[PDB]
Image (cartoon, coloured by chain):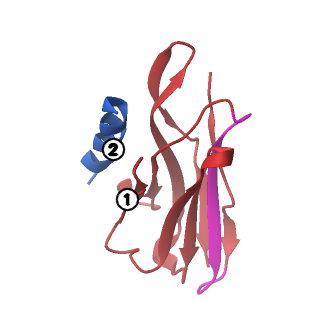
Chain colours: A blue, B red
Amino acid sequence: AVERYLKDQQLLGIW
Amino acid sequence: DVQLQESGGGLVQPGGSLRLSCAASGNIVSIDAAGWFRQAPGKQREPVATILTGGATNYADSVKGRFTISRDNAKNTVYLQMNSLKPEDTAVYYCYAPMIYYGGRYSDYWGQGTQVTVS
């Protein structure tokens, strides 16, 4: 749940 | 530990099509989200595409309409469908998989890259 958030935030930061 | 491995690259004619795959050697770890980068001959590494854990997808402006990112969850593989290539797409393509669990610890992982040429 939190891990999901982390992964996604790593990917969204890229932009 | 794990080693991401890109494949499906290679030579292709202008107007052609390719499908890149990215996976962990031996399927020992799942990939729930990932993204594709590319590096042109004399340019800066840039993001190309992204897919989150939820399924949400984002692309660079120079590839929207042409590329499609996706994943086969049963084989922990992520794909990049590349259509209507043009010489601007000539580059080395890298695979990025964040926060992968292995041997007691999370870590980000990169592939060694794959050549794509449009002549």
Label 2 CA crowd tier, 10 Å (few <14, some 14–19, many 20+): many
Residue position for label 1: B56
Q: Nearer the viewer, residue A13 or B15?
A: A13
Residue occupying image coordinates x 46% and y 47%: B34
The furthest residue to the bottom: B15
Residue B65 on the magenta span: no
> What segment is highlighted magenta in the picture?
B13-27
* Label 2: which secondary element: helix
Label 1 CA crowd tier, 10 Å (few <14, some 14–19, many 20+): few
Residue B20 on the magenta span: yes
**Quarter of the image holding residue B20?**
bottom right
Residue position for label 2: A8
**Chain for numbered disc 2:** A
In x, y percent, where is residue B36? 46, 54
Type of the residue with mark 2: Asp
* Label 1: which secondary element: loop
Q: Nearer the viewer, residue B96 or B90?
A: B96
**Quarter of the image holding residue A7?**
top left
Residue occupying image coordinates x 64% and y 55%: B21
**Circles 1 and 2 in contact, beta carbons < 8 Å:** yes
In the image: residue B79, left or right of residue B43: right
